[PDB]
Image (cartoon, rainbow, N blue to C red):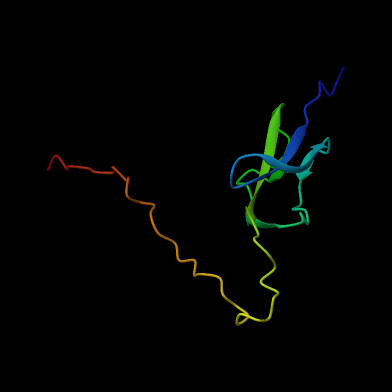
Length: 102
């Protein structure tokens, strides 16, 4: 056994943390994954470990999807109704400090 099952298993889950789609197993040295067209779901983020070199075994690439409530395709109520997305939070915990002896 040369391979020893060093592979990457890709899971496709929603923002609720449940796989809404069939998973895959990338046996390629370059585990390069792709998002799927899930009915009623949109890609929320691409996992920080979605693509790279298989350096370890039992690795999981998990894509997160936002649950789409209708396509906004009623045409009766306006057209583009979805709220904004501006990045809040983060860097509220940095810690870094350095006092100089001299």
